[PDB]
Amino acid sequence: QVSLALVIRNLTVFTMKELAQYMKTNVHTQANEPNSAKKIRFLQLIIFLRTQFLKLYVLVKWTRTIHVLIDLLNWFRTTNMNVNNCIWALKSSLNSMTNAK
Amino acid sequence: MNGNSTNNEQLQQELATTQDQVASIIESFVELGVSIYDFPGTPEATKGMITNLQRNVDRLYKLNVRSNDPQSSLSKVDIPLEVVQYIEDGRNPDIYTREFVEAIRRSNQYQRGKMHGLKQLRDSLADKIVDEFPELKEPVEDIIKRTS
Amino acid sequence: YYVDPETTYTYQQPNPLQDLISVYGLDDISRQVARTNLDGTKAVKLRKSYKNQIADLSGKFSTINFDWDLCSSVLSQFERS
Image (tube, rainbow over all chains, first blue to last red; front, side, top):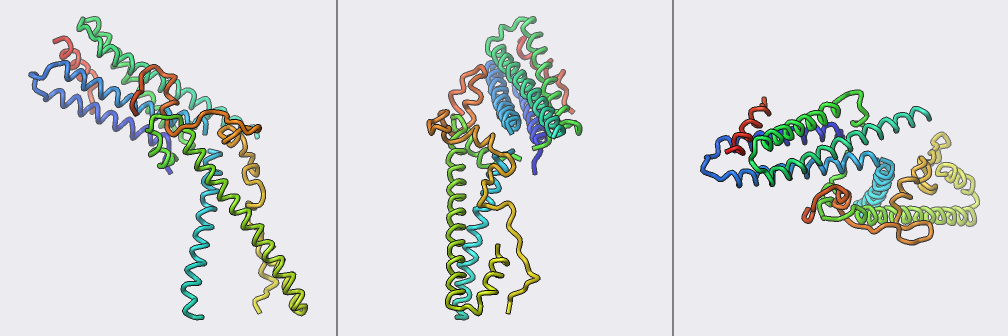
């Protein structure tokens, strides 16, 4: 099982680590690089983090709509491959027992 | 019945609050990007940029803190990996559900048809075993009682 | 030989013959995202991915230990230069 709180925790830790790494890289980057490139890179990183947080927002909205269809869906899938496994087991049993025929 | 309704209302309110906070965070990030793109370099603009960064950091920290509260309902519900693979493709997420529910319904129809077929199979077999072998008629009905 | 009156097999629960959707009152979401309405007409246009759930938000989605104060000051100094 995975909790939405654990997704929030890991995503926020990853965002903090990425921001810290970007800040450190900007710190030890030589000043000869133009500030425009650094600003563009920071904007791109902010856009990526915003996209990740918007994916999380979609997971929040999904969980707000949500489990009923997912429970029925999983139960029907379990029945389906249980039937398939029963068929395969029957075929294997006949293949094995044909020798004893 | 009332407890389930109360727990659903709490979970809906907590997720609406979470949605509003994340939407505010996204709007603040959009404003931050707009300010960065159109930054004039004035000290007032720099102070506004610092304030916006601090507000974004505080909002992100608040989103994490409440979500780890043991009294929050936000922990109550996994995510499908097939959905995580499909969702990037620039669209409105309905064909994965349509086609997979169609497969589910096909499997259910196959199950029902095979159940009906097996039922008629064993009914006919019991009838004929009774017919040509009356002496075994009594266990056969018990067999039905053993199956049905 | 194997006829054991003490060995009784119960019905599998839930019974697949019955309407398994309505066993636990699970028809609301199924009706919400059903393929077709009660009249058979298409309800909503169908697609694959999360993009249209973010269209209401502003933007153009064409393609789809730590000292915060020190970093903010560094960014301010870099921008003011």
